Image (tube, rainbow, N blue to C red):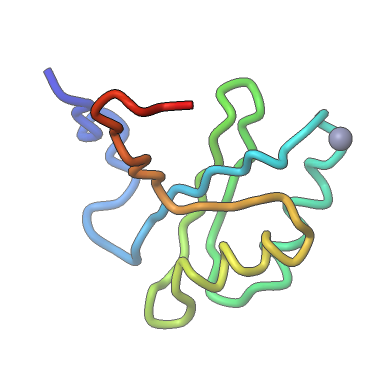
Length: 95
Ligand SMILES: [Zn+2]
């Protein structure tokens, strides 16, 4: 029955949380490096690196900093970052 994020209910309605897909993510020793990039950014409140599920979550104020800035920062390191990939849903042509 849907994700029902209501379970966590981290915040009632503050800032704008965004999810980034880091494909260029390898090992776990890069954790510190990944966190360092976010630290450099301003407006970020908190973040966590989940390699086990290959997912990255970060909470920041859209006004202070937009998701594009976070994704761009990751791109600099060349770790390939994307905000919620919508894929393309091919009819039948898929490599
Ligand atoms: Zn590595």
